Amino acid sequence: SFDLLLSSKNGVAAFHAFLKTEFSEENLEFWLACEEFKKIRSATKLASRAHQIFEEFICSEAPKEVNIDHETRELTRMNLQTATATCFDAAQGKTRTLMEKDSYPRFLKSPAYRDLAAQA
Amino acid sequence: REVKLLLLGAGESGKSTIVKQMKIIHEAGYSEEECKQYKAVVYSNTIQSIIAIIRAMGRLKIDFGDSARADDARQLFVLAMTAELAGVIKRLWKDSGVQACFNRSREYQLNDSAAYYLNDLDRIAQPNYIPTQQDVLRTRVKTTGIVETHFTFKDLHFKMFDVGGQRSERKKWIHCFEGVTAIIFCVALSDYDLVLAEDEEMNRMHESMKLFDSICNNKWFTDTSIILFLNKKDLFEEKIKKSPLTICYPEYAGSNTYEEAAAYIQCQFEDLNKRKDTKEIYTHFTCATDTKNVQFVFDAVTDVIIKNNL
Ligand SMILES: Nc1nc2c(ncn2[C@@H]2O[C@H](COP(=O)(O)OP(=O)(O)O)[C@@H](O)[C@H]2O)c(=O)[nH]1
Ligand code: ALF
Ligand SMILES: [Mg+2]
Image (cartoon, rainbow over all chains, first blue to last red; front, side, top):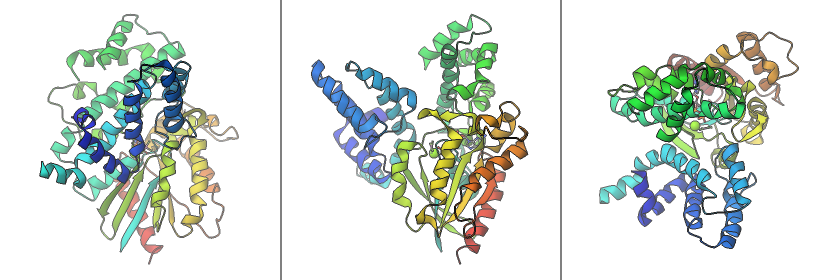
């Protein structure tokens, strides 16, 4: 499963190295930015952190801008108006699917992993 | 004699499908095991297509022909293959309100393979179902990043780099611009009446044109073979009598028929060339999902990549 990969320290780092090879690491980063963000109980830190995550990965002039459609983008922008813990669930699902469907299967057929399973 | 080749183009123009057609042509087809791996995608492609139409009905305010479909729609959303879901999906698809919405897909975002999968639900929904080569070809997965794949045709070895077409992916394209032998630039002809999935204010064809102006005339590619695939011709053919090209080109004085409108698109792109004396856009009308056609076009391309590089 893909859910196992995303749960382990080793797995994530290995998967990152691969995504770097295909210039799509921004996906995994955001997804990890979202799993930290939602643990925040304070409504101020959420407030600020939401502007940070949105500024880096979502925004149309974003440095690590992730590939999501117009609807999911502008929804996440209206979810900022009051940043709760779920603010990015939509954007985070689009991104998870992007990794699961497209680049996760290539990773399983990569030598990066092929060797580390051969070790396993 | 290793050649470096690029598939560039806006999102959903058909780059990844051309990459699949290499695996089929210049390797030896898909296995049966390899096909059984595309089940999930076909099923998910199908489920996503139909959700897309139904969500558009509440936005566009279109009624079901038969009010009991609301109850299936509910189940659809919650369930997302099994018999229950198939039945739900089938019943939704046959509904006249659903079909009125499907015939207005230009106002929202719908996978092009929708009709193909949905019209074939009986086969797909079977328990012992194994995708066909075409089913596999019809599958949609968003490419994110830059995928390098190596190929050996009859007279050429190819390093072939496939990229994502969406705006957020275009930053990354600069990683493979060095020593580029040829660029196949995909354009989805059927996009003339559609908007971008990443900007609803932006017509997809005007987007491809701006993109093409910038690649065609880019300094990096003075020495690269610019090849222009006018793709999804099959989808365009069955569109054009239903939806007029004036959506995309208000200037257009010609008939909304397949050949003339296709000749017109072609000229628009080809007019973007800023050094026509010295540079030649090699144009081909393609159906990416039609192996035979992509086989014939790739022979014509290869010849240009010999003539212009030896
Ligand atoms: N009927 C038809 N479908 C196509 C054609 N080209 C691409 N498709 C389908 O349209 C979708 C987009 O193709 P894809 O290669 O994934 O787009 P990409 O983002 O440019 O790589 C896929 O589901 C393909 O099966 C074509 O020429 N004809
Ligand atoms: F340009 Al794409 F998936 F939309 F390769
Ligand atoms: Mg692709």
